[PDB]
Length: 236
Length: 48
Length: 265
Image (cartoon, rainbow over all chains, first blue to last red):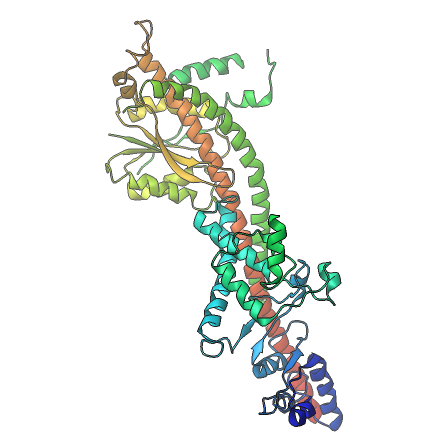
């Protein structure tokens, strides 16, 4: 990747599968050399190994390597030295899970464990930040709002309350976007959707230009362009 | 004696032919007692 | 220690969940008897209500409140009380008759004096005609129900079988029959003392309705309480489970530290 960047100025994307299996392999590599593995049964050379790895990925004036990596934990233990140390280097965090996957949702990315330290009001603009914050806020309220309605009665929703419901549940559907590879999981051939159409869609759903269109007519499509087709078929 | 006491007593006396369901028989009896109270301290309950 | 004190307390929460679970299943059985009874009561009542409209509904006070003797019904006991007390501002020396041990407790505190008559046996024996009739009879002699111009009933309305709204209504006084057109719009000659029989009969029929509606709003709130308890215990199970587990990981780590030091020796 780095050859590409340094001498041909290219933008590249570097995957890793488990960085867990890099820690686990690293435990072994320490121990054989004579070291005592302490880091709660894991290598002591931990910090440096992550540091080399996650500081060879940076932006030069030629190009930039960027890395998407997969981080998995030893049985969901976050206590341990390894998960905290990994999380330390990462500029942002994107959290994907299987619970989300069973609801016919690809991207199965959970929008309340999707957070960045680059989603600030200076990095991405003033607009982008406000658009993300209202789209974040709707879901957050929604989950809470269902809790006491259920206990009090059946559906006891107000005009005010169900404005929040409409908006929230339309937004949950709008996340979807079939992938060619994930054709099987949606049951629907792939789509390709861009950064501009991510933006357009959310401004509109906010303003209730897409509170004219039911929940099922956002289901299995992504961006603005795509959903023009679905609004048309829903009506006609 | 309330009117509805009087007539209740009529309903009850009749449950002294037993051609009826169980809820009916229940309704004409109760185990309830009333704790009498002074204007704090409590005078002894007399059966309701 | 730490470990064991997490672990025993966790058992407490687990036993509590089981007890609240069992009790809520049982609540669901009682709510159905409570509803059936309420329908028949409310329908009997409706026939006098046709009357009372056409008569014109019209006008010391008495207060009645409705509870079971059993507790665990959430905030029925005290919310209903809170509405009793609000209308205790409209007369301090009003005589409150408390139907059920649980509502008795809150009113007794604010004024010990106003507890004059109270009712044991609501929880063993569901709302039925016998209770209401005997309670209507004793009201007239002990409480001066009849010679009062005001009588009002407080209870919890079962708007739906998963909800409760506290509500009040008046128990149509003999003064009301007298001075509303209904010796002039409703006929009797002098063949019966129609005020002194009709009042006494609708003292009970309304009261039975208040008793059956309350038992049903309450038991419905109790299912809710017992459900909410089960959830608070679940949250607590998960949260203490983590706190135990981290301790075990520390103990395993300390054992491994002893193994590392021992390996150096």
